[PDB]
Length: 435
Ligand SMILES: Cc1noc(NC(=O)CC2CCCC2)n1
Image 1: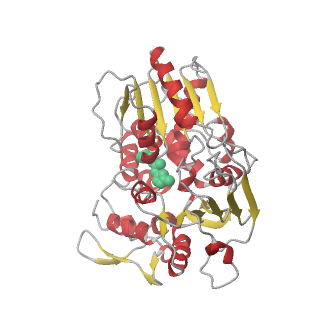
Image 2: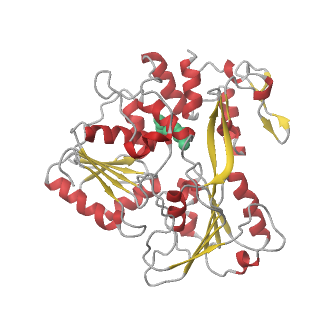
Image 3: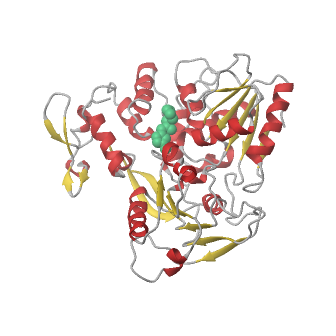
């Protein structure tokens, strides 16, 4: 496993103990061999759970999700997927880790795909070893993998709107349900319907995950309404998963705008991970998985793989060489390696628009490659009229940094900047020069 030029896919079924049993074995083995090691957690929630499984082992925790005084002599680093890729993009020294361990290595967010591309390229160059930990490696066709205890799989019509009748099985349940919805706004409507029915609902999304997930432990609940973010190692004590089997897909249209297409079927990997939230207790057979559609390989043409190429094109590897995508997922995008390579100043802008600016990768690239500096926000208002951002059927309005009320009308339209109320609120602050 740990010998150089080796990439190992640890593809044990969900709940088989890859994180709490195998990972500590690997780490103390790497420490014994004096292997400089990075451990990549998908979320800060998983990072904290890793500290529990690795407590007592000398691990440097490069995340504020853990309150640990470090000795400085640790050769094992732990950080989130996004942090790894961020540090590669920034002008700071990143060690050339001899061992690279990515947990929940199926994560399809751009910074996770890029991290796999960079790591797998170093392995292919014979410079490092890597272990990708996931029950669902890229290209999985099995949406019903093995589990610790038998699961009741039922294909059933699943609501995606509020309902008044026809779905008694949803509310008649007396256990705890994790419900995968295609979007935040879709989850809002389902959540309000359940709450009106007397249910206690917790809602999880990417922006609220590292805070709202604590509620699943601190208070009692009946339903968790979650987007696909809970595919990344989120553990619940539930006995039922309701799966719409649907997701949104960011799609670049004509190379000039990003739309959120769908909802449309999830991949087999996503369906397996959603189902894999339950059936994890061998002493509690008969957890239920209700799914409301089929699977399809909807990661092809998905904007995240193009955005991953935008990131990797701007990460130094060796002279002019450029890291390739991890080969099992390299065909999901039609992109020329290097075509998004920016020069020094435009690359700095690109990085700042993604970090401080909190813009989607694709949008950050359009602005940076147009030669616009980070604080120049005139592009948020000089787009075409079809690019007018709407909220509550009225055009969105902000006060510009000059003190002028203007309609939000970005030169490049990325639907992710206004996918829900919170997203648009953040983009309005950006357009106003507030960060
Ligand atoms: C999903 C999604 N939304 O935005 C992003 N941005 C990035 O992954 C860029 C990386 C990560 C941190 C800074 C550099 N991914």
